Amino acid sequence: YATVSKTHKTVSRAYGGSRCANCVKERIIRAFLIEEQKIVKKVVKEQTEAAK
Amino acid sequence: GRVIRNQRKGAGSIFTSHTRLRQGAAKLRTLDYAERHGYIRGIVKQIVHDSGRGAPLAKVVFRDPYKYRLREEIFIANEGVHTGQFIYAGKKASLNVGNVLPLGSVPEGTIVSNVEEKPGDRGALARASGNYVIIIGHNPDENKTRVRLPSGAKKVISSDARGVIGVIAGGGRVDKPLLKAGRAFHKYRLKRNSWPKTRGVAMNPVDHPHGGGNHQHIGKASTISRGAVSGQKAGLIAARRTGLLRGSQKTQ
Amino acid sequence: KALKVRTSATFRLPKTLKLARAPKYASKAVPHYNRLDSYKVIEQPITSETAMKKVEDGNILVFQVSMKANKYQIKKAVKELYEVDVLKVNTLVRPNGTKKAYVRLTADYDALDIANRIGYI
Amino acid sequence: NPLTHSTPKNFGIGQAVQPKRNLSRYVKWPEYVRVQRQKKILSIRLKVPPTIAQFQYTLDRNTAAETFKLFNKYRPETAAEKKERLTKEAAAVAEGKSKQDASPKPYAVKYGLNHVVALIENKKAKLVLIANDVDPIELVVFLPALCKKMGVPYAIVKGKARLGTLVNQKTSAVAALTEVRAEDEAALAKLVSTIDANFADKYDEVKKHWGGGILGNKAQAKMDKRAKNSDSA
RNA sequence: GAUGGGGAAGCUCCGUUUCAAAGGCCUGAUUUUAUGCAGGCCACCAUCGAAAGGGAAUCCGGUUAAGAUUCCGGAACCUGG
RNA sequence: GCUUGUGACGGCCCGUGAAAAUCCACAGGAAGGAAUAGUUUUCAUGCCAGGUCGUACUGAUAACCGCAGCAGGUCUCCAAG
RNA sequence: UUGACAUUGUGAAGAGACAUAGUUUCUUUACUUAUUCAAUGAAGCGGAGCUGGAAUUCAUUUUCCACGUUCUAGCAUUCAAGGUCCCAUUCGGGGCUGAUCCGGGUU
Ligand SMILES: [Mg+2]
Ligand SMILES: [Mg+2]
Ligand SMILES: [Mg+2]
Ligand SMILES: [Mg+2]
Ligand SMILES: [Mg+2]
Ligand SMILES: [Mg+2]
Ligand SMILES: [Mg+2]
Ligand SMILES: [Mg+2]
Ligand SMILES: [Mg+2]
Ligand SMILES: [Mg+2]
Ligand SMILES: [Mg+2]
Ligand SMILES: [Mg+2]
Ligand SMILES: [Mg+2]
Ligand SMILES: [Mg+2]
Ligand SMILES: [Mg+2]
Ligand SMILES: [Mg+2]
Ligand SMILES: [Mg+2]
Ligand SMILES: [Mg+2]
Ligand SMILES: [Mg+2]
Ligand SMILES: [Mg+2]
Ligand SMILES: [Mg+2]
Ligand SMILES: [Mg+2]
Ligand SMILES: [Mg+2]
Ligand SMILES: [Mg+2]
Ligand SMILES: [Mg+2]
Ligand SMILES: [Mg+2]
Ligand SMILES: [Mg+2]
Ligand SMILES: [Mg+2]
Ligand SMILES: [Mg+2]
Ligand SMILES: [Mg+2]
Ligand SMILES: [Mg+2]
Ligand SMILES: [Mg+2]
Ligand SMILES: [Mg+2]
Ligand SMILES: [Mg+2]
Ligand SMILES: [Mg+2]
């Protein structure tokens, strides 16, 4: 693999030559959603403190 | 006389464990800051077969909170714990199967496994294919906790001593007839050189306390004292009763 | 006033000044002369019948050469002791513990000429 | 403001690596360090005998400063000065013909352990400083009692090196004055009295007081709260 | 199987990362100059142990009394620079 | 068809059937870098270099071990109708 | 294996004798610095304080706990972004705070 043009060892995507794309799909989705929920977790218990 | 077999095993030559294929030593996390002021999460990236072990191991990786990098521990899989699962380790940690908690924090009745003897000895009690321990009570002043082991012996250890929620996997292993010589053959193949066993009664006197005679017979009492010296101790050492156990067992 | 700040919990041997040798007298009075000059490198020509045949046909010079000498040292010294240029040197230790260099000249030089210039034939 | 942003890092278990912090409390020192700290500690935890614990009671910085001030005037001859003196009598004395006395009478501090001791013993010393370091403490433990017995006023001082410097040694263990120029007698009898007040006088009393028996402050507090709660409910 | 060690009258026995102050890379600082200090790392702490295990890369043709995937011829490939 | 190679599967286990050197990838983004001309050697082409030791032959009813050119012993590949 | 002596020190309650002053000796139970055992690239110990708050006020606090993470098989590193101070404004770099205080007893 050290005698080979870099294109043979990759595909042109996020996390290219390293995870199976349906894997990338998954960890994008979960990334977005968990980062979002983080917002829904904060402001919600920001209300808890104010309504207690 | 010759050095009898049980003596030879101690100098550990052709005896020593068969070590080579074994996932590594099973252990709890070191008892750091996190685990004794709060809790810390990790994922079981893999549950797997240790060789010469009854119960499945559980590869469980954590973050290292003092350097950006992953640090993987090796757990004995309790039952029902599964890949992808989140695992919690700490004093202030919820109480579900698979988590590791100090015995001080689990209500009595709790069932736990791979428990520490002293706190922070990374597991040492009930680690075997099936076993567990029952927390049977606490004493807050001098924070001890009382538990029952698989032996039925009750023991009191410190409450900071951790142990993991649930029971060990591989349940019922000993319930299946080994069936033939080969199965035990392959059983001990990956344990140590202890099988097969010649009977001391089948040897000559040079070889064993029992050896010789023109009939096969132990010739003297086989309940042998504690104080008995090396090369004497073969048979029922320190035996306080002997014979078929009549009547119920179970520690009263 | 106050103390040091160490962010690491590990201690190490303080990197200390490594002073260099300034001998009060000398190693060996006189440095040794070159222990393997060209002349010591290449010992005799080889002139077995079958050796020669490589000189007519092959453009190759055959030298019983120093055991202590490698493919480089052989090339440089055939080069300098004989005016010629070398394509390639193969070597082999004889079954009598003497080393043989199949030395092959480049196509500018006619080995057979070069052979009975040094004077064997 | 700009297109800059506040992102404050959470460090509360479970999340974000800890930052670099100061761990000087937590470092694996070289054993020689451990041994020398543990040594000092062990020496305070035991119950040290009165004829040792009478040291530790050192002179104070004010008084001492006055003592080193006075003694400095009396340093012993220098490298140069002696060579310089010797030719002011090699030449001078031998020819002009003095009694080996075209040199003035020397007024210097006395030092060297065996030296000072005979001095004390002969009641010729008039003010003696004993060091407080001195590792074979035995070398010097008897010095208080001696002076006391010989009725020679004494003071335990900080600095076996500070004793050393004033006499051109690295270390000295003891400094002593026997002689003193009259123009200095004033300043000395002063010092003798303050000194005697803190040492020779208090000596008999120091003789009964075992030092040490001091807890580490983990355990010192552990009972400072236990003895605090148990009694006063 | 050395080493900091610990045993042993001693030949030597134990231990192999273990109660140890265990060591070296990247380029920067030089433009007195050759390499001092400046960062930041990295704590992995001997070595021996396989011509059947792992492993960078070559083939065909021709040639000798006796060598050849090693020479001759043609055509390749790997590694360093 | 035979021999061997190989794939997708299936059975078996209280047996679930090495390790390290080594090579690549990706996450990361410190950094360096263009318009009067920069960046680029994981694209092509081009130059120099590759040491040391072994290389013969027997491998057995005579080249090894059994006092020997001993009916014994001594690990393996290729395999026609 | 069992006893004695040595290693072996510090307190407190109770015994034990000049025959009901405390030198000494032992039973019990404290101490931690000797010895002992464990873990860790000796990382967060001990003590105080800020905030919350249950708590019930017998003058105001006498106290007790809390004092960043739990639907998810993602992501967490460049002495940290931010804030403020300095260099003399260059690119770069430094202090402090962000991350409270004290004791250096690694636990
Ligand atoms: Mg591709
Ligand atoms: Mg492709
Ligand atoms: Mg072993
Ligand atoms: Mg067997
Ligand atoms: Mg049997
Ligand atoms: Mg049997
Ligand atoms: Mg028999
Ligand atoms: Mg017998
Ligand atoms: Mg018997
Ligand atoms: Mg018998
Ligand atoms: Mg029988
Ligand atoms: Mg020709
Ligand atoms: Mg060769
Ligand atoms: Mg003078
Ligand atoms: Mg050894
Ligand atoms: Mg090797
Ligand atoms: Mg090999
Ligand atoms: Mg051929
Ligand atoms: Mg030939
Ligand atoms: Mg041949
Ligand atoms: Mg060729
Ligand atoms: Mg060519
Ligand atoms: Mg190249
Ligand atoms: Mg076959
Ligand atoms: Mg399988
Ligand atoms: Mg790859
Ligand atoms: Mg290229
Ligand atoms: Mg080289
Ligand atoms: Mg051959
Ligand atoms: Mg052959
Ligand atoms: Mg033959
Ligand atoms: Mg033979
Ligand atoms: Mg034969
Ligand atoms: Mg620690
Ligand atoms: Mg920068």
Image (tube, coloured by chain):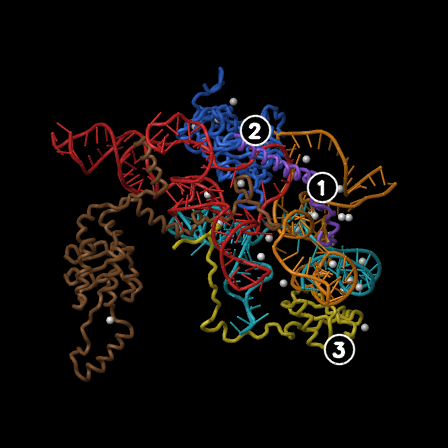
Chain colours: A purple, B blue, C yellow, D brown, E cyan, F orange, G red
- At label 3, the amino acid type is Asn
Chain where mark 1 sits: A
Residue indicated by mark 3: C116
Q: Looking at the rendering, which quadrant does residue D168 occupy?
A: bottom left
Q: Which mark is residue A20?
A: 1
Q: Toward the viewer: D161 or B30?
A: D161
User: Is residue C39 rendered to the left or right of residue B115?
Assistant: right
The three-letter code of the residue at mark 2 reads Val
Of tags 1 and 3, the one toward the viewer is 1
Local SS, label 3: helix
Q: Residue flagged by tag 1: what amino acid is it?
A: Cys
- Where does the C terminus of chain C fall, quadrant-wise? bottom right
**In the displayed structure image, the side of residue B236 where residue F45 appears, left or right:** right
Is the residue at mark 3 from the same chain as the one at mark 2?
no
Q: Could you say which is closer to the camera, residue E17 or residue A9?
A: A9
Residue B97, numbered circle: 2
Secondary structure of residue under mark 1: loop
* Front one among A18 and F31: F31
Q: Residue A43: where, in percent of width, then height? A: 59, 35
Q: CA distance from mark 1 to mark 3?
A: 73 Å
Q: Position of residue C65 (x, y in %)?
A: 67, 70
Farthest residue, direction top: B247
Residue visible at 69% across and 67% down in the picture: C100
Mark 2 surroundings: few (<14), some (14-19) or many (≥20) residues within 10 A? some
